Length: 180
Image (tube, rainbow, N blue to C red; front, side, top):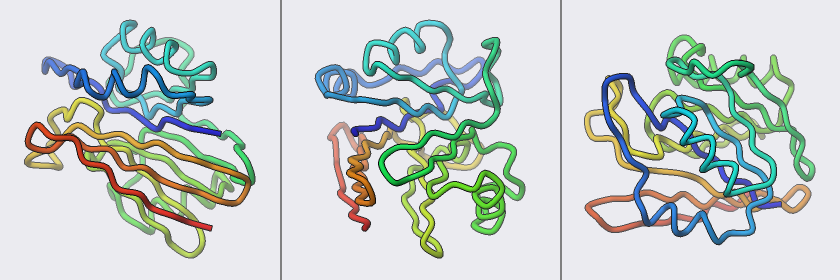
């Protein structure tokens, strides 16, 4: 099971484009599932996501207006129950304890959130908290210099691998995080 974790595409009145390199890479992968944190540019973004994987999941973002978008979603992949939400609702923002409360609320092994516009992989108390950052490196009050980012998860049962992709200084960088 290969899962593309992406989100935070658009900010109102600010134009952002997904880097072509990310698109070229994403277009050929055998990506089974897409978990999107929300904040889509519009229908164009959804069309793109539909091309990447058979199964696409999108939660409601701060600026999302698409009808039928749930605030939270829970998907089971391998041995992991995955919780997904935009993360603007987690107050205080990005706080470990606040996120922990939501993870417990959703009763999931993995909690995926965006909002911060900073990609982060963290394991706390045997639970995993993942943020893929902004795919387009969109403006955020929270971060001075956001960079385009996304995550690819390789899950085989209880084995979790995170591929953190970021575009820094015009050159793509990738880091691998292993969890058992």
